[PDB]
Structure formats: C-alpha cells, structure tokens
Image (cartoon, rainbow, N blue to C red):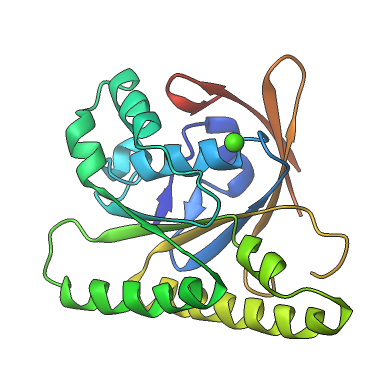
Amino acid sequence: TIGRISTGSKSLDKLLGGGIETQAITEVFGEFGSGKTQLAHTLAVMVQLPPEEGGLNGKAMYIDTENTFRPERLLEIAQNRGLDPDEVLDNVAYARAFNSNHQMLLVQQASDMMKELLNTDRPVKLLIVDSLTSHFRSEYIGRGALAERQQKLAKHLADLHRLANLYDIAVFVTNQVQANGGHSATLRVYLRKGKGGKRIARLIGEAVFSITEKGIED
Ligand SMILES: [Ca+2]
C-alpha cells in the first residue's frame, strides 16, 4: 500500500496496516532469534521491488552495532525469491557503528549522502539500525549514567525521525525489552518465538509468521 514496504508476510503487513511506513520509525523488540534481524534482512530486499510487489524501487542502508549484518543471507533471500542476487547486494549499503558517538554521527553522514544523491533514480528508501541501544547500554554504566544514556538515545531517535521526514525513508530499528524506560519517536512491535519455529508479532493485535529460505513468510 501507499508509502509502505512489505515485510514478506501478508499477516504481518495486515497487523502493521500494510507494511512498514516511510516518514516513520518502526521499532521491533525481542530477544535473540525472535525474527528481528531476519525481518531487517527481508525488508532490505523488499524495498527494492516495485510497489505492486511490496517495495519502493529503492535502496537500503544497514547500520549494525553487534555484528548481525549478513550479505550471504541477502544473497539467499534474493536467489530463493527469483531475484538477481548481485543487484540486491549492490542496493544494500552497509556501515558499522563503532560506538554510541559514532552511531549518532552516522545519522548526519547518511543525511549528507542522501542530499548529494537527490537526482538518483533509485534513492535510499529504508534505513535499518540493528541493536539500536547496544552501544548506549555498554558505554553509560552505573545508576548515575542512566539519565544521560536516555537523553542521548532520545536525541538519536529525534535525529532519525528528522532523517525519515527529510528523505521520505522508512527507519527500521531493532531493540530488546527493557526493565525501565520507555518511542514518543515510533510504532513499537514485540516479537516472540512461537510453536515449532513460527514467530509471533504484537503491537505495543497479533500476527503469526515464519522464517524461511525466502526470509520472512506467513
Ligand atoms: Ca532474528
């Protein structure tokens, strides 16, 4: 549907109101193996497709903080969906965020890059930040550092929301459930492991999906 990227699952798209939205931040929470990273890799392929096939004829940028990006997985999803894998890999730009300060600087650097590429036929339409809070949690420790950590995270989310609106891109971020917090910034989706190997998504009703050779499916 209009301005949305399909997840690869019709059930998950229905729950999301058609898929992930441009000009917005979608935040997916869950433990390791819940489907969050698999969903990010599938969306990096889906965004490239025409709108009738659930994409935006776009490119993706994947920012990693905990070594989760797998080009071979994109290659596999592309091959299994009948798409050209070299084209798919050429359209997903990868950058590692080394620490929380660098992670925050990457938003302005991505903004500078998208600006110069304004005339391009295939613009970036999806920005993924996998494990959004990992560097903030490991660099701000002790009870006294919590307020500062939250303040820096809020500023980072505000910079991402501004990026989504200046370039009409979908921002997709992954995180883990927090004992304290907190959004204001988003659309929050919790992912769980289901029976057998299915995964369940819930908005913070519910939708069932699976992890296959094609990435995310029903
Ligand atoms: Ca996963």
Q: Quadrant of ligand 1?
A: top right
Residue 171 lies left or right of residue 17; in this view the side is: left
Q: Looking at the picture, tell me which residue is in the foreground, 175 or 194.
A: 175
Rendering coords of residue 185 (x, y %) = 63, 73
Is 133 located above or below residue 114 in the figure?
above
Residue 27, image x, y percentages = 62, 57
Answer whether residue 98 is visible to the viewer in this image. Answer: yes
Residue 98 lies, with reference to residue 190, above or below; the image says below
Query: What residue sits 44% from the left and 19% below the top?
Result: 213
Quadrant housing residue 44: top left
User: What is the quadrant of the C terminus in the image?
Assistant: top right
Picture layout, residue 205 above or below residue 199: below
Q: Residue at x 45, y 68 (%)?
A: 23
Above or below: residue 116 compared with residue 129: below
Residue 57 position within the rendered picture, expressed as x and y whole percent measured from the top left: 24, 49
Q: Residue at x 13, y 64 (%)?
A: 120
Place residue 89 in its image quadrant: top left
